[PDB]
Length: 122
Image (cartoon, rainbow, N blue to C red; front, side, top):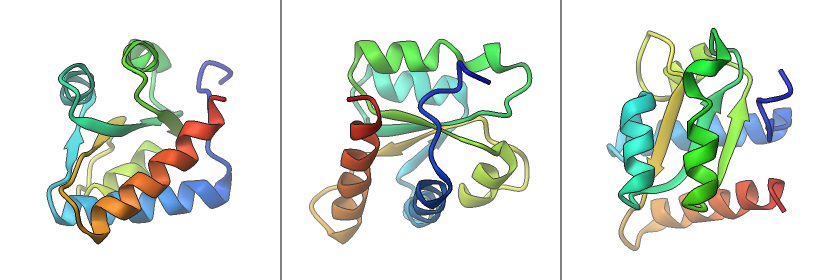
């Protein structure tokens, strides 16, 4: 789907899902479209991850648009099911926000990845 841009190449997908898992382990994730739109508006989201196989895709298309307006880096991954697993849940997750952590190695990881995702949009 061409509206599912930027689309993370496979290596990046892996790095995203592995970091989501770690973040969710420390509750540095919001799941679901509503909480994500909200994290972005309130300046709480370091970056946003969207599921390209969301059905229909129109459900989440306000997210890239709020992200652009708030300059929150966002990226599409191919699978909402995979993203659910990484968030620690057995149902699909179509959107999630990786939150801002206090100084720590986790923050450092999150920040590093945020910069990677930033550069997709440049």
